[PDB]
Amino acid sequence: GINPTLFIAQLINFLLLIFILRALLYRPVMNLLNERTRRIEESVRDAEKVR
Amino acid sequence: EQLANARRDYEAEIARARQEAAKIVAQAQERAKQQEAEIIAQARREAERLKEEAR
Image (cartoon, rainbow over all chains, first blue to last red; front, side, top):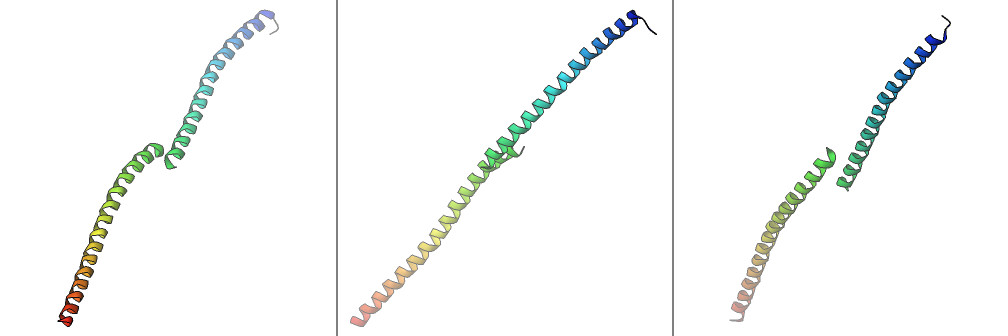
């Protein structure tokens, strides 16, 4: 298996998979950031309510 | 949930504590006023006894 066409096709498939993974991980990073912000806001509200 | 329930419980407990403290202070003031009225009646009885001694 030594040819340039197979390498080009595999590179195209790898680029498509990389784009899909980039979208998938862009979703989870935003989800984690939203969860952390919500937790921080809830803790601040609890402290303010206690005071 | 602790923030929300803490705000709600702070409001409810402030209202209930104010009402209960007002009621307890009113009862204690009524008891103290009854005791003071009894003391004043005892002083008036002592004054009447002094008037009887003067008579």
